[PDB]
Every structure is written in structure tokens, then in C-alpha cells.
Image (cartoon, rainbow over the protein chains, first blue to last red):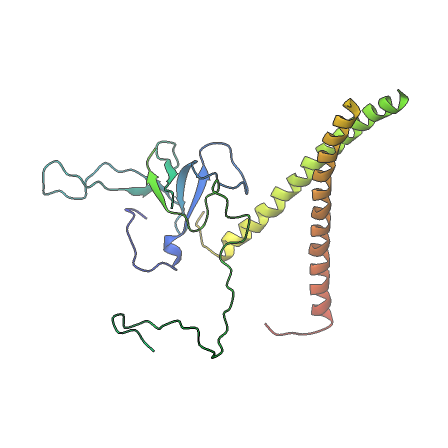
Length: 86
Length: 48
Length: 48
Length: 48
């Protein structure tokens, strides 16, 4: 329920994410390729949030930071879907 | 006939022997517009 | 001119008709809301 | 010409209305689908 990780194979329900707009809502409205997105987890209804603790605690000025999921919703964390052309 | 450099591979020829090519849909027409988040896109995930 | 006045009155009744139109897609989000609710129920187990 | 432009706008609203029309026969296949489902249930026992 915390600390998003990478799983090797992905048909399980533990890797299903669902997303809701920051702006006005919609039931089916053709997500327009650049909108801001808040990520909601499915198997445990929990919202992603940016933890400030570092992954690597051994070397100074650490480049690796952690992320987590917290069960209350806020507008601090809202990932953007910026695309790359083929 | 398997390829020699790649072990799990097979050649595609154009000989007279019969084969069936089943059409498996992945993306219907009019879902291939560039202004829509599609099911095969590559994206990078910027925090706000 | 009486045709034009009747057309203005008909435009009023047809704007009431298109209010019934957005009532029709109100029924649309009701139907797709319950459909997606049972879809999430069958293809997922989210706690409340 | 203002009548013609009003008629073109009304043609657009009536094409939205006939989209609500095929929405009406969407409700038709929903109703006859559940009706034929219970009909097969009462006049037949197919296993699942």
C-alpha cells in the first residue's frame, strides 16, 4: 500500500491504475494527450504522493528519491502526461 | 526452418504452400487521432 | 410573417426539446455510470 | 437568408436529435435483449 515498485510481469490486478482529472470531470471524453492527471490505485483505493526521503542513505547528496501512496486525496501531486512523438 | 543466429525464430517465405493470416484488431479507425491518449503511446510522466 | 412568428414559437418549443436532449445524455451518464460501476466490480476489488 | 441560416442551425440540432434517435433504439436492443434473455430462460435451460 506504499512505495511504488516495478513488477516483472503484469496481468495481475496489483498493477492497475486509474486516473481522474484535476479540471472539470467527465464520463468518457477523449483524454486530450496533455492533461494533468492524479493517479489512483485500484486494488487498494490509495492515491500516489511524493515522499521526500531518499532511497540511498549511504552517499552524500543523494540523487534517488522515494515515492509512496497515501489514502487521502490532495492537489499537491498531479502528474502530467507529456507525450513524445514517434 | 529456424534462423541460425536467433534460436527462437522462423523465416517468412513466399512459397506456394498454404497458410492462413488471421486479422486480429488492435486499434479501430478514428481512434488513431493524435489529440487523444491512446493505448500504445509512449509518454514521460512529469510531476506537476 | 405569420410563418416567421410560428417559426419563433417552434424554436422555443425545440429549445425545450433540446433541454430534453441534455436530459437524454443525463440518462446516458446514469447508464454508463452504473455500467462502469459493475465493470469495476467484476474486474477489480476496491475497498470502501 | 436569416431563415436559411436558422434552418442550418436547426438541422445541426436535429442531427443531434437523431443521434438521440439511435440512442432510442439503443434502448430498444437493451429492452429486447433482456426480454429475449428471460424468454430463453423460461422456454429453455441452457448451461453456462
